[PDB]
RNA sequence: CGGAAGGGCACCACCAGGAGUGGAGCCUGCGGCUUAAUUUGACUCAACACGGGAAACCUCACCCGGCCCGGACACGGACAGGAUUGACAGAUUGAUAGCUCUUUCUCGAUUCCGUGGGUGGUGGUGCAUGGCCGUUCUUAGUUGGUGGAGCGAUUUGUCUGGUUAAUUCCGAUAACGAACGAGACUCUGGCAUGCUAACUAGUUACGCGACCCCGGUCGGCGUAACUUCUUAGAGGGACAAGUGGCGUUCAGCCACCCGAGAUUGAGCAAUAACAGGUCUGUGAUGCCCUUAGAUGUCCGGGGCUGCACGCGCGCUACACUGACUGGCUCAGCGUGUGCCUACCCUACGCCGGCAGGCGCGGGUAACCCGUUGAACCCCAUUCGUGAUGGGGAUCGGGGAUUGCAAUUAUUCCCCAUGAACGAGGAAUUCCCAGUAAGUGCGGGUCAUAAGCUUGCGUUGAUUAAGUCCCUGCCCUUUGUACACA
């Protein structure tokens, strides 16, 4: 059956191979280098990193965004 | 249905604890009346139990505005091997 | 928010608020004595509730 | 001692046999009885259309449901009248024993 | 009871209670020769009696379906445990029970017996029972 | 079946009349004509205030857009080296929908993608169905069994006639005895100074208290008798039973005493049928359609009301048998705090002219609103035949309440505006006693809410106790080359 508009195709997401290993810097010792600050947020503490956007920071699930 | 497994296992736990279960057809009911200890939307109890039914694990009987779900032998065996329990214990319907 | 919009509209009154306790439709409802049964469903089950044609 | 037994029933002759039975039980247990005071009958009346559609002559159904209320007041310690009222129950009537 | 509702609303509440109970039990015990219900709310007992023709099928294997039905009764209508007691019993001279005979014909038609043979088979049993 | 004859019955027929409808204004349901849409079912009685349909959103189908999966299930690439869900700015929109262009964080095999198969559906066919309903018809009609008559299909009973609300009966009679429908039956109204009972009903007497001059008044206060008044149980009572007429002397009809009634009103309802209505009452339901850009469903906007038009049901009037202003005085049916469900009935004390606001209370109700101080009517004024103080359409301005929201005014209040209408053409409707009509009060719908409908009491008649003239339907006789008639 004929419609008015040529439709909007649904948002297909950009799936990526390992966005994880870009969360840490590797050392040649047996030590570490944590890239993005760890928010001590109510529920989402240690393993939950903050977002590093071009204008502000953002904590994922508690939604705790920060002006630079 | 897209489901939280936490809520899904809590439904399966109560279903076992008492073999048969009742659910009103009201998909826009915020919390389930019985399991108010858990945050269970009525939609999710219905969708879980109708998914159980499709394979022939539960017995579906419908009145005016209430689903009635009795447990079968197929459901008994799936539910017990799934929750990873002692094989001896059974629903509240069997014990004399 | 999808879940801020799905059941966003308020229902405290009108005939979209109240529902037939049998067939679930929204015309010719009996609300007298807290029945909440549509007139056709009432008339079907009327003798089982206790209502009797005398006069 | 001043205790209030009320009987609320949809059927009449059922209610009358229960009213008789409590007078019998009271006069046998040798305690003062106030006879069965008959409160006015309430007639729950609902009048609907007959036709499911609206393509007929306008004929209405007149559904009635009478509900009858008796009460007997006795001068008796709780126990003996409690054991009088624990026997000879039928499905029609409903009991309320009120102390104060 | 502190909710303390009118005797008018109380009796229409009891009216719809029996009406749905009967609907549910006619839908459930349809094939297994179901005749009807009865309630006897005694002091702190809801003695809820069922009348059937094939009571062995409905009370089932060592009382599976009875406790299943007592569970959904207490669960849906919101009753106290211990207080609700179901009792399936056989109705006398089934030949005269219009419910039992109508559902018997229905399941002979569901089997696939001839229509004049189904009706005359039923009608002959009704008459020799003493209608 | 007849364009042949005859006989019956009915205020959905007439006669005698009453109220009217048709005329005017508005409310409201149809067609029409506009519109993105103004969704639609029904069209003589048996469509058109009907779908309980009084829709501001929802309701809600219609239409202009925007989210959404609630696609179970078996199978197949995909896969944690992550399938996927959620997402704050910013442009995006109507939206604080992460729907999106563009950000980077979150989530953990329940996703998402094809193959089937399922689903939901106020989508389609009521000319595929069930159920319920309406109509023929609430008219009086329908059928065995033994017996009789015919070779037989069939017929008699079920009839010329009188009578009845009635195929109701008694009469004649090859029929006798019966069954369904009529009746009987259930509820209801009127009667009991007889009976059983009453602090959730009274009364009478009494003691007290207040006021007028021993009495009088009190719904002012309080406790021994009793059941007249109120309540609701059991029996009683009325049967054309008494008398006088008429009649085949029957069935029964008319009048009159006595008597609370000399026909109170409803509920139910046959055999057989209709292509009557409903798939938009149902998670009654065959088949078809659709099934992700949905005919599923949620969301926000409008529409269901649009106005040269023609119909139908109602409301208010056209005035003095009246309008206005005071004063006096009397009802009966009900209903009332909710499952999800939020919203109940209201007395009383202050505030405001009014609609209202605030305060403490009673009530799950013969207990509180309540002795339900209702209207018409009644008594006393002002008006004075003038489209007038008749009538209140249309329009302007302000103020309250309900709601998340009132413009296309929800409703209500206050001032102002003052339309036709001077009793209604053809045609046509309902109705015989506590009836018609006037009059207001409750129930339904209901957050708000009656010009509708369903009940209730108050005031309360004129005319008739007849008929087949009119419109219908029903029977008997007769005729037929008809029998899907």
Image: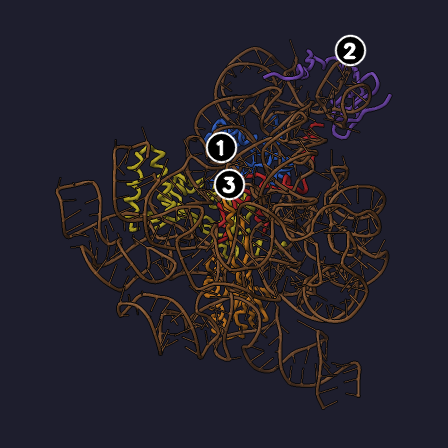
Chain colours: A purple, B blue, C red, D orange, E yellow, F brown
Return the x and y of residue F243 as percentages of the image width and height: 35, 78
- Between the C-alphas of marks 2 and 3, the distance is 87 Å
Label 1 marks a residue whose chain is: B
Return the x and y of residue C49 as percentages of the image width and height: 50, 50
Of A32 and E86, which appears nearest the observer?
Answer: E86
Label 2 marks a residue whose chain is: A
Please give the name of the residue rendered at 39% of the width and 45% of the height, measured from the top-left corner: E99
Same chain for the residues under marks 2 and 3 in the image: no
The image shows a total of numbered marks equal to 3
Please give the name of the residue rendered at 48% of the width and 45% of the height, measured from the top-left corner: C44
Of F329 and C17, which appears nearest the observer?
Answer: F329
The vertical placement of E98 against F209, above or below, is above
Label 3 marks a residue whose chain is: D
Binning the other alpha carbons within 10 Å of mark 2 as few (below 14), some (14 to 19) or many (20 upward) gives: few
Q: Which residue is mark 2?
A: A27
Q: Which residue is mark 1?
A: B58
Binning the other alpha carbons within 10 Å of mark 3 as few (below 14), some (14 to 19) or many (20 upward) gives: few
Q: Which residue is mark 3?
A: D55
**Which of the numbered marks, if any, corresponds to residue D93?**
none
Of F346 and F147, which appears nearest the observer?
Answer: F147
- Between the C-alphas of marks 1 and 2, the distance is 56 Å
């Amino acid at each position: 059956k004929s419609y008015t508009t040529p439709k909007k195709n649904k948002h297909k997401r950009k799936k990526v191979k390992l966005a994880v290993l870009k969360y840490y810097k590797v050392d040649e010792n047996g030590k570490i280098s944590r890239l993005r600050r760890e928010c001590p947020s109510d529920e989402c503490g240690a393993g939950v990193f903050m977002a590093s956007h071009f204008d502000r920071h953002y904590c994922g699930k508690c939604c705790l965004t920060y002006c630079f | 249905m897209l489901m939280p497994k936490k809520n899904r296992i809590a439904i399966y736990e109560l279903l076992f604890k008492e073999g048969v279960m009742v659910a009103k057809k009201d998909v826009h009911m915020p919390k389930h009346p019985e399991l108010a200890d858990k945050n269970v939307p009525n939609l999710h109890v219905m969708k879980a139990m109708q998914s159980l039914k499709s394979r022939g694990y539960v017995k579906e009987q419908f009145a005016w505005r209430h689903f009635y779900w009795y447990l079968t032998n197929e459901g008994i065996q799936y539910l017990r091997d799934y929750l990873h329990l002692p094989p001896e214990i059974v629903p509240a319907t069997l014990r004399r | 928010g999808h879940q801020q919009l799905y059941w966003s509209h308020p229902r405290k009154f009108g005939q979209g608020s109240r529902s037939c306790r049998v067939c679930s439709n929204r015309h010719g409802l009996i609300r007298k004595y807290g029945l909440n049964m549509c007139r056709q469903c009432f008339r079907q089950y009327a003798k089982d509730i206790g209502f009797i044609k005398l006069d | 001692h001043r205790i209030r037994i009320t009987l609320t029933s949809r059927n009449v002759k059922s209610l009358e046999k229960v009213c008789a039975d409590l007078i019998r039980g009271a006069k046998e247990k040798n305690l003062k009885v106030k006879g069965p005071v008959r409160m006015p009958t309430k007639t729950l009346r609902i009048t609907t259309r007959k036709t499911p559609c609206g393509e007929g002559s306008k004929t209405w159904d007149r559904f009635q449901m009478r509900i009858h209320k008796r009460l007997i007041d006795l001068h008796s310690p709780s126990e003996i009248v409690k054991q009088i009222t624990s026997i000879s129950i039928e499905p029609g009537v409903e009991v309320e024993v009120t102390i104060a | 009871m502190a909710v303390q509702i009118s005797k008018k609303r109380k009796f229409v509440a009891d009216g719809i209670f029996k009406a749905e109970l009967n609907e549910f039990l006619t839908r459930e015990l349809a094939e297994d020769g179901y005749s009807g219900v009865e309630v006897r709310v005694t002091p702190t007992r809801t003695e809820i009696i069922i009348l059937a023709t094939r009571t062995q099928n409905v009370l089932g294997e060592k009382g599976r379906r009875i406790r299943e039905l007592t569970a959904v009764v207490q669960k849906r209508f919101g009753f106290p445990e211990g207080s609700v007691e179901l009792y399936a019993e056989k109705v006398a001279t089934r030949g005269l029970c219009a419910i039992a005979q109508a559902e018997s014909l229905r399941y002979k038609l569901l089997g696939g017996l001839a229509v004049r043979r189904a009706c005359y088979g039923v009608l002959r049993f009704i008459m020799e029972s003493g209608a």
